Image: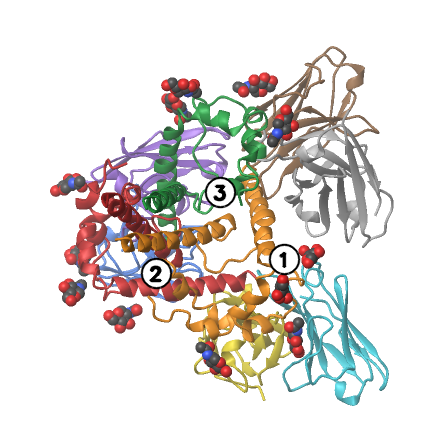
Chain colours: A green, B purple, C blue, D red, E orange, F yellow, G cyan, I brown
């Protein structure tokens, strides 16, 4: 499982988006019998929290998920070639750390809950 | 008490881009779905468009599906209809009405309960 | 569209039964048939909804009914003020929503 | 995250159904280093059990999920206006505690497994 | 919950595929207060790992999941009647233990990631 | 040994509501999908409807899709067909047959293996 | 529907080849073409299924074959008891399922 | 520098099964979507088929949807078109071209950027 | 298909504006209208893409524009080497992709 882990860390975002399963499979597994257990418990919570995010968004069970949130040029004005072909995910995460929680809120609030309510109302027509 | 009052109606040419606006009072605007229904001068009633209570789901007849655009603002209590590329068959009195659908949490409202004065449109 | 008789007549105090015929996909699939009364120069008014149900403020003299792919509006106790164009409205699914019939001229 | 938690506890069920993400995000996180760890583990199991229910039903990844189980008037004869507009979720849960496991069984047994088998058979046509 | 557990272990695979919820619901729950806690933690990880597999495949939230991996006669030449009507799951698992990781790799690599990328590209047309 | 025996067949008027019932014996009824196929007196065979082995999936031809209703009871071994709003084009000998589909866990049965005596219907 | 020759003839002991022509969406897309033999006054019987496969109890004299968008029923060793109406059945997808051809009158 | 060179073109009869192959050079083949577009001798241009950069998504016009098959090999830089059941309306010069779509991670390429010499096909 | 004028003419140094008319579902729904120039005996060449955008190597004399459900190709500074058949290409959704217009004969 470990093999290939973080190998595309220095690759472009496009090239590094085809190895998502390699990172995904590496997120899940005498006081030293307690502390290690705590670490195991910690890993589970982190995994579940990320999965919870994917579930409050319409992204449950997916590694690549398309959404209805428009991109804002304030978050980033770079082209697609300057993000996917000429840029790595670490650089992108360093720039967009500043805006992550606005995008997360837009993902959580407007799009998924309005879409879910609209499916609730279309299903009773 | 429910008072629907349409405006923006008048005369336009083929290819025109005409905007109507229906103002509502006397009830909770955001709690009801709204529809536009048209009546040609010499014919009966024809349903044109439907918008839900939140303004997120819109439905149209095939004959206007790519030309008409229903919209609503729930703070201002204003329903609106923007018609582009108006055709000779679109000459009619347009009425705004309350009803046509409801959310899953309400009882069925598959009917038009309240109606407007009407607004003549001559293409 | 629904097929509806172009005009009917009835003497005062008599009872008339306007009819309305539709395909099986609309009247015969959903129990949502409503009737509207439009006086000349004014906008329609919902006399009946859900086949047999009356909006408040509407007199008991107006009643509705269904039979297979057909609906009917029984107007009893005809008065001079009932002289109006009556219209059907049937819910016909999700790919199309409301289909109206032609007007029925009621004379007294 | 905590902000707004249980705020719609006294609101109507309709109004309180638009805040589901606020409660959802608050379900997931020297003998005192063990007992607290046990509590953390307990929370995870509860979360997973609820998610497991949603997965055995056709509701995985959703906060609002529509089903094919008809409502039974024996469970409740109240109208929709008397449930969603004039009633809170605590009152509803107190009445329907008595019937919860019948609805859960119908959700689990007939609808989801018959639907899943019917998709298994439609996919081979 | 326990009732009926593993009851179809000796039944045919077809008959035993209608009881999947019974096994699914039984996977989730002083040094003896630590060791038992470790066991609880262990169960969670196992559950999550299996769920993770189902998520890297296109099978999240499902107990029966159809895929685009063709069956290979090298893995098994038996008919459908000799697998579903005349065979149990234990016998099938004993034969196909030898081939499980090839099928798992094909499930993980070609089908799901190519399908996910193709949906990523269809959604922007 | 497989014996299919239809009943309920006779004569009806336009708009009629006619119910046929096919009784099966000699094999496991719940293990096979069933179909109804009709033959007009002067024409060839036409497939009408299909129901799966569990009675949960039903398929019809467009010409009868909103009028016919195939159903099955696996305890009583009875296949049934309820036709509403019968039209003049529905006059035919109706046959019940075993086959037409199978579940994912079985081999393909895209054919009608066993057949019934037939039942005349005159609209 | 499938196009099938209205009638064919053959002397006893000779071999005939009934033909059957369909669109590419049905015979040319799925290898599920079956043949039925119906005697007058009786119900059909599955002579062949899956193009080339015979139900048990059916004599070897009946064989089937496909060629592009065309299917065929080769009946060798013709006997007096083969005088029947033969029908095609092709599987044509999920939006429609079974399409039959016209009958072929076999005389001996 | 981009050089597209079609081959496999010639003459065939109705019902023929004709294979064309377009060889590409001068650019990254696997990075671009490819299309086939045809021009009848006396008419204008008609788009025939589209294949994405990975060769997993294929699109066709309704008139050829069940007869033509676009395919690509990215190691050999070869685009190919297999047409079965060729009809009289399929007589044309077929061109291979770069473009027509792109993946979500690229800019829109809803146009045909580079073109081939062409290949005559007479049914 | 798109409707395009069969032929236009212009004297050298003058400017011509080839037109192109489509339905609202294609030109009026997507801003993806491209123009191609095909000399006799050769294959087309992308003069313009995305309505107003020119591939590199293409002279500035060629420009494009849109107006509702109509597109246009303004060719200024006409030269003898511009004598070619011009074609439209509009993107028209996912159930169909590219619709071409007829050719426009340019003479100088
Ligand atoms: C590192 O960058 C070079 C170009 O400088 C590239 O060829 C190589 O593939 C990159 N490595 C990885 C792991 O992506
Ligand atoms: C983008 O962000 C700015 C603030 O940075 C905000 O004012 C603006 O409305 C946003 N635009 C959109 C389209 O959401
Ligand atoms: C977009 O692409 C152009 C191509 O010339 C490049 O020079 C430019 O830096 C890019 N712009 C942004 C904002 O990334
Ligand atoms: C966000 O703000 C921090 C400073 O608070 C800065 O380092 C970071 O680069 C900012 N974002 C961008 C896109 O520059
Ligand atoms: C509490 O009830 C009042 C009406 O009595 C209502 O206006 C108010 O919004 C309710 N509070 C909440 C939090 O829903
Ligand atoms: C509703 O519940 C009663 C028992 O409380 C049961 O007998 C009845 O069949 C149920 N109705 C439906 C429609 O499931
Ligand atoms: C349903 O609504 C009516 C409206 O008058 C109300 O009085 C009644 O109590 C409600 N019924 C139930 C069973 O909740
Ligand atoms: C269910 O039964 C309990 C007593 O066992 C009772 O308190 C509860 O209210 C019952 N359910 C209903 C809907 O009354
Ligand atoms: C065990 O096998 C017998 C046949 O030998 C069968 O009838 C029975 O149902 C099987 N038991 C189970 C639990 O499937
Ligand atoms: C099946 O497995 C063998 C090796 O056991 C392999 O060579 C062959 O290509 C496989 N077939 C398919 C169709 O994948
Ligand atoms: C498939 O079915 C036949 C039916 O006669 C059986 O004898 C045979 O053993 C089966 N083959 C395999 C490979 O399981
Ligand atoms: C896989 O190999 C083992 C021995 O390494 C053997 O026991 C097993 O049966 C093999 N698989 C099959 C299908 O025989």
- Residue lying at the far top of the rendered structure: I13
**Disc nearest the viewer among 1 and 3:** 3
Q: Identify the chain of the residue marked 2, using the numbered disc in the image.
A: C
Question: Which residue is pictured at 39% across the width and 69% down the height?
Answer: E5
Looking at the picture, do discs 1 and 2 lie on one chain?
A: no
Name the residue rendered at 42%, 30% in the picture.
Answer: B18
Does residue I28 appear to the left or right of E27 in the view shown?
right
Pointer 2: what residue? C31
Give the residue at x 59% y 89%: F1
The percent coordinates of residue F101 (x first, y second) are: 57, 70
- Cα–Cα gap, marks 1 and 2: 47 Å
The circle drawn on residue A24 is: 3
SS category of the residue bearing label 1: loop
Picture mark count: 3
Disc 2 versus disc 3: nearer the observer: 3
Depth order, front residue of D108/A33: A33
Q: Does ligand 1 reach within 8 Å of label 3's beta carbon?
A: no
Query: Assess mark 1: CB under 8 A from ligand 10?
Result: yes
Q: Nearer the viewer, residue D19 or F67?
A: D19
Label 3 Cα crowd, 10 Å radius (few <14 / some 14-19 / many 20+): some
The Cα atoms of the two marked residues, 2 and 3, are separated by 51 Å
Circles 2 and 3 on the same subunit: no
Question: From the viewer's perspective, is C56 left or right of G12?
Answer: left
> Is residue E27 depicted above or below I16 in this figure?
below
Q: Identify the subunit bearing mark 3.
A: A
Along the viewing direction, whichever of F18 and E15 lies nearer the viewer: E15
Percent x, y of residue I28: 55, 31
Q: Chain of mark 1?
A: E
Q: Which mark is residue E70?
A: 1
Quarter containing the C terminus of chain I: top right
């Amino acid at each position: 499982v470990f093999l290939g882990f973080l190998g595309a860390a220095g690759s472009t975002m496009g090239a590094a988006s085809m190895t998502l399963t390699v990172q995904a499979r590496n997120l899940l597994s005498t006081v030293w019998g307690i502390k290690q257990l705590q670490a195991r418990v910690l890993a589970v919570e982190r995994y579940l929290r990320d999965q919870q995010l994917l579930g409050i968004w319409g992204c449950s069970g997916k590694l690549i998920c398309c959404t209805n949130v428009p991109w804002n040029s304030s978050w980033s004005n770079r082209n697609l070639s300057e993000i996917w072909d000429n840029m790595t995910w670490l650089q992108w995460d360093k720039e967009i750390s500043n805006y992550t929680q606005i995008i997360y809120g837009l993902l959580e609030e407007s799009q998924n809950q309005q879409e879910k309510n609209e499916q609730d109302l279309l299903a009773l027509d | 008490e429910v008072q629907l009052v349409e405006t923006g109606g008048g005369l336009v040419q083929p290819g025109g881009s005409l905007k109507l606006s229906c103002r509502a009072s006397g009830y909770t605007f955001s709690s009801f779905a709204m529809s536009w229904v048209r009546q040609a001068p010499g014919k009966g009633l024809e349903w044109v468009s439907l918008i839900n209570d939140r303004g997120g789901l819109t439905f149209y007849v095939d004959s206007v599906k790519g030309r008409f655009t229903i919209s609503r603002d729930n703070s201002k209590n204003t329903l609106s209809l923007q018609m582009h590329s108006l055709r000779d068959g679109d000459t009619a009195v347009y009425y705004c009405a309350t009803g046509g659908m409801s959310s899953a949490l309400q009882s069925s409202k598959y009917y038009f309960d309240f109606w407007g004065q009407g607004a003549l449109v001559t293409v | 569209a629904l097929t509806q008789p172009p005009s009917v007549s009835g003497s005062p105090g008599q009872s008339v039964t306007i009819s309305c015929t539709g395909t099986s996909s609309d009247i015969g699939s959903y129990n949502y048939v409503s009737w509207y009364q439009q006086h000349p120069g004014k906008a329609p008014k919902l006399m009946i909804y859900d086949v047999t149900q009356r909006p408040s403020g509407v007199s008991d003299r107006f009643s509705g009914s269904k039979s297979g792919n057909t609906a009917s509006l029984t107007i009893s106790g005809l008065q001079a003020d009932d002289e109006a164009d009556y219209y059907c409205s049937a819910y016909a699914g999700r790919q199309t929503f409301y289909i109206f019939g032609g007007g029925t001229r009621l004379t007294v």
